[PDB]
C-alpha cells in the first residue's frame, strides 16, 4: 500500500471556487464548500454569490411586509413555539378588518407585497382568507400567503381570490428527519403541497432551516439539490433557533456562518430567485440581515404585525423587539437598504427569468 496524502487546503478551496464559478454543481463540490471552515474561502464564496445577485437580480431589495395574523396552530412541530402542545403562550386571532386595515397601512408606507402568515388556524380556512386576499388585492400590491399545509381546494380558492405567491418552507428534505420533527405530517405531504401550488400558478417559495437537531452536512447538500431541482421562485433560509417551551429547547442553535453559506450557495444555484435575508438571520447576529444582503439575498420582510399581537408570535426567542413602535419596521428597512447602497423595489418584485 502507498500513501494517500491530502491536497493542500488552500489549493483545494480554490478548486472548489472554480468549480462553482463554472457551475459544476456536484454533490461532493457542494459538500466540500459547506465543510471548509476557512475565512478566506467563505469570503470568496460570499463575493461570488453577491456577484451573481448583482448580475441577475440587480440592486433592488424588495420589501415584503409580514402580518402574522394568528398564532393558533393545529400542528405540533418540535422546533416551533406555536406548536399546539405549548400551553405557555397566549394565543390570538386578528379580525379580517384588523388585517385588511393593517395591510392598507403597510401599502401606504410603501410595501409592494403583503405577506399573510399564521399558524395552521382552521378558523380562517378557506373563506375568511379569500375575503381578506380580495380586499388587499384591491390596494394594488402583490399578496403572498404562508399558512401551512391545506387541501388543493383551499389553495385553488385563494388563487382565484388573487393571491400571487405562497411560501411553504420545506424545512428539511430528509424525510426521516422531517417526520421526526413534524410528527403530524411528512416531507411527501409538504412536497405535494409545493407541487400543487406551482401547478395552480403561484410563485412558490421553499427553503430549509440550518442546524436542526439530527441534520448533517449531507442533509444540507440534499436541501440545496432539492431547491435546484424545483427551480423555486423564492427560497427562505435561516438558522434553527431553539425555543425553551419546546422539546428541542436544549439543542444546539444553528450556525450563522453555515447558514450564510447556504444563502450564498442558493443564490449561486438559482441566480434569479428571490432570496430573503430572513428574520432569524437578524435575530441570531446583530446586523445579520444586512450581512445576508451582501451574501446573495435580495429581499427583506419587515415585521408588520401590530401590538399587542406581535410579541405573541413567538416562533423562536428573540424574534420580536418590543423596544419600538409597531410601525417602525418599514421605515427602518428602508433606511437599512439606503445605507447598503441598494434601492427599494420599484414594482412587485416577482421572480423573473433572466439567467440562461
Ligand atoms: C460590519 C460589516 C463590516 C465587515 C463586513 C463584512 C466583511 O467585510 C467581510 C465580508 C465581506 C463580504 O463581501 C460581505 C460579507 C462580509 C461578512 C461583510 C458583511 C458586512 O458588510 C460587515 C460585517
Ligand atoms: N425554532 C425555529 N427557528 C427558526 N425558524 C423557525 C422555528 N420555528 C418555526 N420556524 C420557521 O417559521 C416558519 C413559518 S411558520 C408558517 C406556517 N405555519 C408553516 O409552518 O409553514 C416555518 O417555515 C419555520 O421554518
Ligand atoms: S412551524 Fe408552522 S405548522 Fe409547525 S407548529 Fe409552527 S406555526 Fe404550526
Ligand atoms: C415572497 N414574496
Ligand atoms: C422571513 N423573513
Ligand atoms: Cl421573497
Ligand atoms: Fe417570498
Image: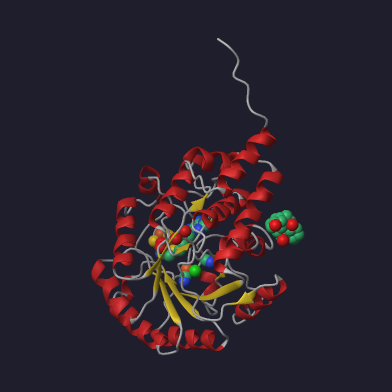
8, above or below 151, in the image: above
- The location of residue 270, given as percent across then percent down, is 49, 58
22, above or below 164, in the image: above
- Rendering quarter of residue 184: bottom left
- Rendering quarter of residue 298: bottom right
- The location of residue 131, given as percent across then percent down, is 33, 84
- Can residue 81 be seen from the camera position used here? no
In the displayed structure, does residue 191 sit left or right of residue 232? left
How many numbered markers are drawn? 0
68, above or below 79, in the image: below
- The location of residue 49, given as percent across then percent down, is 60, 56
302, above or below 11, in the image: below
Residue plotted at (59% across, 64% down): 55
- The residue sitting at the top extreme is 1
Identify which residue, 227 or 354, lies in the foreground. Answer: 354
In the displayed structure, does residue 24 sit left or right of residue 16? left
- Rendering quarter of residue 291: bottom right
Q: Quadrant of the N terminus?
A: top right
Residue plotted at (29% across, 71% down): 155
In the displayed structure, does residue 196 sit left or right of residue 180? left
- The residue sitting at the left extreme is 153
Identify which residue, 344 or 47, lies in the foreground. Answer: 47
User: Is the image coloured rainbow, by chain, by secondary structure, or in one colour?
Assistant: secondary structure
- The location of residue 253, given as percent across then percent down, is 58, 49
Residue plotted at (60% across, 82% down): 327
- Can residue 286 be seen from the camera position used here? yes
Residue plotted at (60% across, 44% down): 18
Amino acid at each position: 500500500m502507498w500513501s494517500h496524502p491530502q491536497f493542500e487546503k488552500a489549493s483545494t478551496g480554490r478548486e472548489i471556487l472554480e468549480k462553482l464559478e463554472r457551475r459544476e454543481f456536484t454533490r461532493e463540490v457542494l459538500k466540500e464548500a459547506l465543510s471548509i471552515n476557512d475565512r478566506g474561502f467563505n469570503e470568496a464564496l460570499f463575493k461570488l454569490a453577491d456577484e451573481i445577485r448583482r448580475k441577475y437580480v440587480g440592486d433592488e431589495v424588495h420589501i415584503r411586509a409580514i402580518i402574522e395574523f394568528s398564532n393558533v396552530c393545529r400542528k405540533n412541530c418540535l422546533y416551533c413555539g406555536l406548536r399546539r402542545d405549548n400551553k405557555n403562550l397566549k394565543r390570538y386571532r386578528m379580525t379580517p378588518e384588523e388585517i385588511v386595515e393593517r395591510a392598507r397601512l403597510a401599502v401606504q408606507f410603501g410595501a409592494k407585497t403583503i405577506v399573510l402568515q399564521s399558524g395552521e388556524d382552521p378558523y380562517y380556512m378557506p373563506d375568511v382568507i379569500s375575503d381578506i386576499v380580495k380586499e388587499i388585492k384591491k390596494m394594488g400590491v402583490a399578496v403572498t400567503l404562508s399558512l401551512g399545509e391545506w387541501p388543493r381546494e383551499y389553495y385553488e380558492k385563494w388563487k382565484e381570490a388573487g393571491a400571487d405567491r405562497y411560501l411553504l418552507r420545506h424545512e428539511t428534505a430528509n424525510p426521516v428527519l422531517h417526520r421526526k420533527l413534524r410528527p403530524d405530517t411528512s416531507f411527501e405531504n409538504r412536497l405535494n403541497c409545493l407541487l400543487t401550488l406551482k401547478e395552480l400558478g403561484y410563485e412558490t417559495g421553499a427553503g430549509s432551516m440550518v442546524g436542526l437537531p439530527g441534520q448533517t452536512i449531507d442533509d444540507l447538500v440534499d436541501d440545496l439539490l432539492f431547491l435546484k431541482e424545483h427551480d423555486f421562485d423564492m427560497v427562505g433560509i435561516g438558522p434553527f433557533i431553539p425555543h425553551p417551551d419546546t422539546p428541542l429547547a436544549n439543542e444546539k442553535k444553528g450556525d450563522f456562518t453555515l447558514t450564510l453559506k447556504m444563502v450564498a450557495l442558493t443564490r449561486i444555484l438559482l441566480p434569479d430567485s428571490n432570496i430573503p435575508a430572513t428574520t432569524a438571520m437578524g435575530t441570531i447576529v446583530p446586523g445579520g440581515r444586512e450581512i445576508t444582503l451582501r451574501c446573495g439575498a435580495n429581499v427583506i420582510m419587515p415585521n408588520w404585525t401590530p401590538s399587542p399581537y406581535r410579541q405573541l408570535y413567538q416562533l423562536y426567542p428573540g424574534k420580536i423587539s418590543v423596544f419600538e413602535k409597531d410601525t417602525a419596521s418599514i421605515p427602518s428597512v428602508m433606511k437599512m437598504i439606503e445605507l447598503l447602497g441598494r434601492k427599494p423595489g420599484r414594482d412587485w418584485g416577482g421572480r423573473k427569468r433572466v439567467f440562461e
